[PDB]
Image (cartoon, rainbow over all chains, first blue to last red; front, side, top):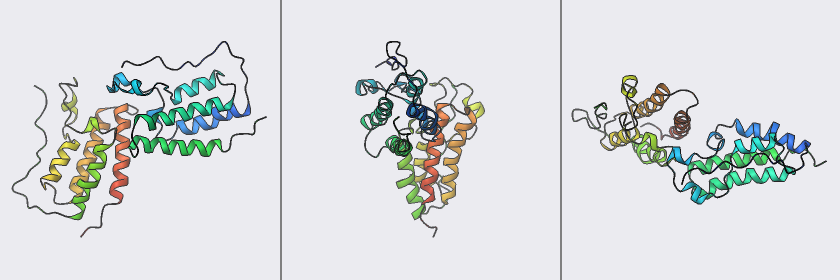
Length: 127
Length: 127
């Protein structure tokens, strides 16, 4: 499989809003995860052509990566903070789906997911 | 063409010994790194002609790879664990020497090096 186009990051056909929760997700959560030692394999869509991984987009039909989440936040793609949280969960579960329990890349995603969970525990109150 | 012969893996004129530390380096450390998802670029000597890296062996004069380290452990090439740990260090620093900060291949090597360091943290006590 060649690579698919990356997920859409702008939507001219939705209303936009900025909230405490969405700003926190960008300025705290994404930033903290981006800088983590384990983040780099998750920062851009898997380049299956470069890695020579023909089965990746045969198996992962809902790809997601931190770069896409960053762009969606910056473009006000999300109306509800849960839409963004869902994208993070898609990125972590994609790693568990493609790989196997106990794999090193899985342990990396698990550490990232634990940190993400710790940070969104502190998301500002829905206002 | 362009590749040197691989590093020597047997040494008939050197005494041999088996130790818990050498056992651990082969059966725990090497095995763990070998199975890492990022291991593949480091499992065999760099084929500079196949990768078209004609300068590789003009820059890297002390090549090292995990396949060599595996053979050296299997052949009792090392008397001291530090000789093996030095070979791992050489393999990682060779990656940093030839490539540049931020390259994917370097980020792979850094992750393997940090896991290697965690593993040899738990090397069994010397005799």
